[PDB]
Image (cartoon, rainbow over all chains, first blue to last red; front, side):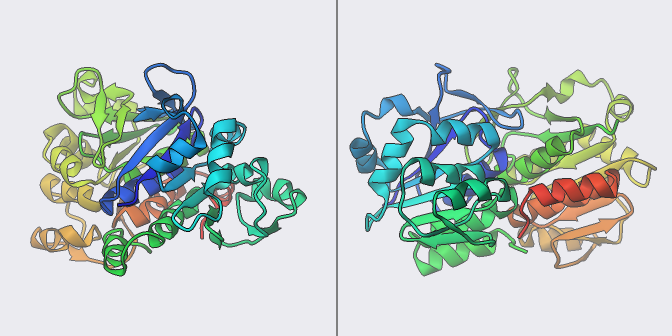
Length: 191
Length: 191
């Protein structure tokens, strides 16, 4: 059974957090929110001011190697300020570098969260992200695709709050059986 | 200054709460989360286990007339348990009945939250909701439309987590200038 880590920081976007969270919960696949921040109660101020608790602090996990024995999917959501913090945290970079190209691991990044590919020195060729980070990614030698969701190797990237459902679904698609994926998909009333 | 109330209860769906929340926040339109439930600290256990503080408890608002003095838009999200609670709370029904067909008031319901139209006795002819409540809506006499969003008078109804962004947008469209609406829309990277 696959387990998912949804990273979260102060300033993480509520929509981009909620889509993969709700999708993996519907799929009955374990998922933990893992806070990168200093609040000792794991209380998070989200990008648009929702105050919510995370399940864990990243300080509970000693290394990317230990992280990899705990989780199979690592998700880095966006929101301007949350993405800045996540993309500049050495631990998150180490996890991303460790997971990349592993046959039993997957990475998701959405909106400004995709800056983590660049900061982690990932060598994928093609990518998407929020149009506001397009310049930054093309400087990193990435070919930017203007579409909701991109997959290269085991890195799923996505554009923004409007694509967070498609992003969560693409991650689920990698680990769910056909019947589980189809059932979850059908339950969402996708447009 | 348009002022939005996003109702929330234990068991409210994370995705359907976060979409209108983030959209109105982007539009710089004031929005409060207003909790209906037993928790005296406004700590809400959401449908898929997120624990989040609401801004207010509905108990702070002495009547539906007083609510109408404070808010112009009332939003009722889904999730099975959350919608059961909200749809069966007379305060919520009273707000919905008061707002219906009133100039410059708006009501939004999504997924199982649409049961509030039936419990409030709203005389709109057409409606949508989650396929899971399709029969029950039909039983109250509504004509069900299989499309993401239905607008009738000043009632916006919508289907499910997959349509929560289209739902939040349709609400925003009624109250924002075309210029503001287009800017918010553009920022979301809608597919």
